[PDB]
Image (cartoon, helix red, strand yellow):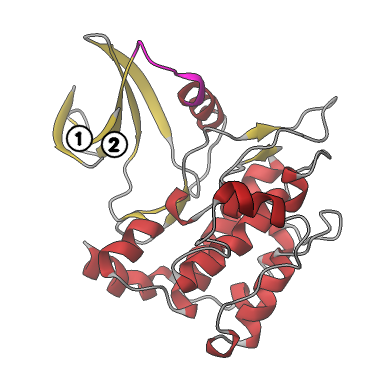
Amino acid sequence: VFDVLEKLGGSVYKAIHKETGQIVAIKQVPVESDLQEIIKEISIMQQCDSPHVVKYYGSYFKNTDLWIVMEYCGAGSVSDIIRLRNKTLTEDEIATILQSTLKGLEYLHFMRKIHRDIKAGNILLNTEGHAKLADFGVAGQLTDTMAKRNTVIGTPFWMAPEVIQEIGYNCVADIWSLGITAIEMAEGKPPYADIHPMRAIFMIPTNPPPTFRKPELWSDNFTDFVKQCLVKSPEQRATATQLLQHPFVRSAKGVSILRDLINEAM
């Protein structure tokens, strides 16, 4: 049923679906492990149907292992691509990638889900250059009787001020994480990266919004895009829908402009 090839990363494999020839990824996890986040991730992906979100195809038991079958993203994460090439991204490459990422967020947020771990390591590119959100293992779900989440969770440098403070928060926590991700893609690491993450988390609520390390390298469009994402007040912060109309994003080139990037990395 599945013809497993090489190890890409328990662990991840490339495989063919012998009934279609379609390539998939199969994550192998031993059943006797902590499956808490695997369970949450799959429950969230099962509810999603979007070309900007990694798809889940199903699960199997095999010799005391659990095999999870998922959409295959050939180029890997944006973070991998940056390491492989040893180069940060250009304004155009970032505008294209984040346009698709924002369509993913617009979809999730309409569906009442907060990803909670947006960062370059969790945006995946397929070989045609289409970005997809992955890794839903700490995602939150809003409901009728729960209009805010309050769990302090995510990855420290990318966490929104309101997520760190005790107050509840909603989907726009992800928009803060996206601004940090824009900086990470342009500069190679998030603000506060050289300081202890348990120290940085206490600074995030009290400090002014982060800026670019070298403001002179970047256009006014890109500079303004990051400013809007990183508005400290959650109630004032732009939505994903609104940011898709931002001049930095709405004029983004087609995915053809990432062909250099993928080819070089792969």
- Say which residue appears at 84% left-offset and 40% top-offset: 167
**Mark 2 packing: few (<14 Cα in 10 Å), some, or many (20+)?**
many
Marks 2/1 in contact by CB < 8 Å: the verdict is yes
Query: Tag 1, which secondary structure?
Result: strand
Q: Is residue 158 magenta?
A: no
* Number of numbered labels in the structure image: 2
Q: Is residue 36 left or right of residue 255?
A: right
Which residue is situated farthest in the bottom direction here? 216
Query: Tag 2, which secondary structure?
Result: strand
Q: Amino acid at mark 1?
A: Ala
Q: Which quadrant: the C terminus?
A: bottom left
Q: Is residue 35 magenta?
A: yes
In percent of width and height, residue 87 lies at: 34, 73
Q: Nearer the viewer, residue 122 or 254?
A: 122
- Say which residue appears at 56% left-offset and 45% top-offset: 155
Q: Is residue 33 left or right of residue 227?
A: left
In magenta, the rendered stretch is 31-37
In percent of width and height, residue 242 lies at: 74, 64
- Say which residue appears at 39% left-offset and 73% top-offset: 88
Q: Amino acid at mark 2?
A: Ala
In this figure, which residue is indicated by the disc labeled 2? Answer: 25
Q: Is residue 86 above or below residue 219?
A: above
Q: Which quadrant: the N terminus?
A: top left
2 or 1: tag closer to the N-terminus: 1
In percent of width and height, residue 164 lies at: 72, 44
3D distance between C-alphas at marks 2 and 1: 6 Å
In this figure, which residue is indicated by the disc labeled 1? Answer: 15
In percent of width and height, residue 162 lies at: 78, 48
- Say which residue appears at 84% left-offset and 58% top-offset: 233
